[PDB]
Image (cartoon, rainbow, N blue to C red; front, side, top):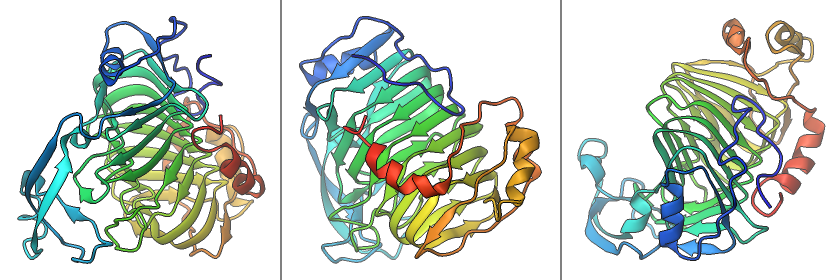
Amino acid sequence: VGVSGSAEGFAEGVTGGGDATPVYPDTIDELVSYLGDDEARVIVLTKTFDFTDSEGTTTGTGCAPWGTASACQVAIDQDDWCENYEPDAPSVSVEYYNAGVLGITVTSNKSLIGEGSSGAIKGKGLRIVSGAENIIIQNIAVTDINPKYVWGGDAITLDDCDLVWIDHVTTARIGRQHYVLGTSADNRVSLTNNYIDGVSDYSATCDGYHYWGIYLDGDADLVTMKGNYIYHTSGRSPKVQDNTLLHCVNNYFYDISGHAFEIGEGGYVLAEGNVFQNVDTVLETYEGAAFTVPSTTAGEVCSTYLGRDCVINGFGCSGTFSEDSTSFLSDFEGKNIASASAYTSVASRVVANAGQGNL
């Protein structure tokens, strides 16, 4: 048992803990120790490690900027957020678990893989920060992190790192972001075959659709998103900006009541071979640059930089998405480009291979 397959895209070459002898944590204490260790580790999760109440509960005053209905989620007044973002929002009492607020620190040369459909962390997410590099997280589930509270916790956090490969991971019922990319450079990252479950009891849109999906706000990021299953979200799917070059290929965006893409200044996106099914608005904000392969002929321009043609996207009951900025394509020269299949096989392939347990 060990890491199955290999990273495709920008993070091609990750080895994680390498061939170090696998360790099997019995307690949450052991898991935390191994992840923040100094040695190259290959940690195998054979069960659910529940952190929910491991750090107690905090009672305080937050705010409800999205309504006071029970289907809506509220915000913990972190960093005076309510005061300088929603000064008009009604104050509300909040009670949340401390464990979710901050994730488990992951250090360099680590390989965290789950076994079958058993490996899972509940109530606390992961946090790859402080320059950690060469990390592989595969076949695990990170769920239930203060669902009702924005600022109650993020599932996967990458802030100042390099060579990170997250594959076959399932995230669900998270208070805020499922994936947050730094603020500092995260460099080479490959998100593949992940299942983002947006079905939640509390949502910022008060309708059961998770709004805080993926947030790419890295300072110098090269992110590859392939074979991912983005499901039931209402926004930030994904939100790209800062200085991020996103290669969005062969992903399945399904049932998005709201919007998917939010491209800001400094965000560059190459969307090819994706399938958008029941996505009301595919592109909301567009201040950066994107090439969505408007047609097959248009896909031929990729040849010079990617070494091959780009593949068109498929649309079913979805809004349009057609942008053709090619100026940034030169940035792909000398990088590891993930291959692309036709969109006709994406839907079927993703739902069968995306997420934990489908490895």
